[PDB]
Image 1 (cartoon, helix red, strand yellow):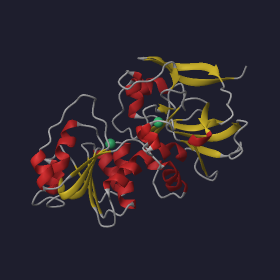
Image 2 (cartoon, helix red, strand yellow; image 1 turned 90 degrees about the horizontal axis):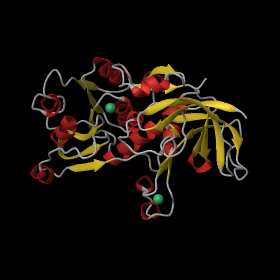
Image 3 (cartoon, helix red, strand yellow; image 1 turned 45 degrees about the vertical axis):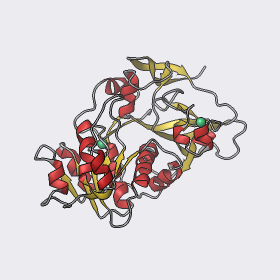
Image 4 (spheres, rainbow, N blue to C red; image 1 turned 90 degrees about the vertical axis):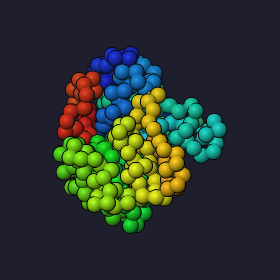
Length: 343
Ligand SMILES: [Cl-]
Ligand SMILES: [Zn+2]
């Protein structure tokens, strides 16, 4: 019996590396030897039971790798191909799916959450979830397709286009990837707000036209105020931090007729005040953005053509053995994206 290492969430709070069997693909599965799998903030929430999962389960939903076996019914992608996985499996039979809102599937199952995922030497990927990418690519770049796709969906919803002005709240990987996508989509002012000096510097290396530090003063005044960067406000505000203060400020950062996108996850049940008078009289849009419907191929293409800076987003590369400790502890100060490299 051939074995592999895998980072298993045994039950809420209980995570460790175990030896498990190398899985055997069903007729429509690919078996993929993982080249890299990113750690997400969602993985820490999964560990602590703050998002639901189906333990015992191998975590990891931001992965790419080389196909080593194809199921009998797969004629399309052969061993040797590189793929990135879309972890989100929609059912195709519920009212959300039948209306094309596959991200809102009522029966959604996610690789790395309800099914064994990418923090392992090998992972099963149903054919429909596999997106081929070039073999000439850096082996780890494919791991960014999922987070890029989530950000690209948010940028699509925002209406960013040539000449837009944009404020991005939060200096995590989501904020930084959204800086890059804002510029690619045509925004000519892209401002990132974060208290972390290291993240402001990185934002400017990857396309931010300016950055602001919320410690130095009121961000609403610094951006949208009379002597701010963009007096009267920006076209588009994308809240990426999932923090109450910045969700609250987002509408006041937007110009009249502007758009706020809620891309960051604030804790369930937590409440924030809006002013309905202002939303109406300044004709604002407030839009939720959820995961990656119909954007994984575009994201994979952007990675394939080198349109996005990926290397600067990688703060650390770790082994499977190191993953449980990194996931069990809070994100480090200079952490952008940690990649788990199974070998
Ligand atoms: Cl962020
Ligand atoms: Zn469905």
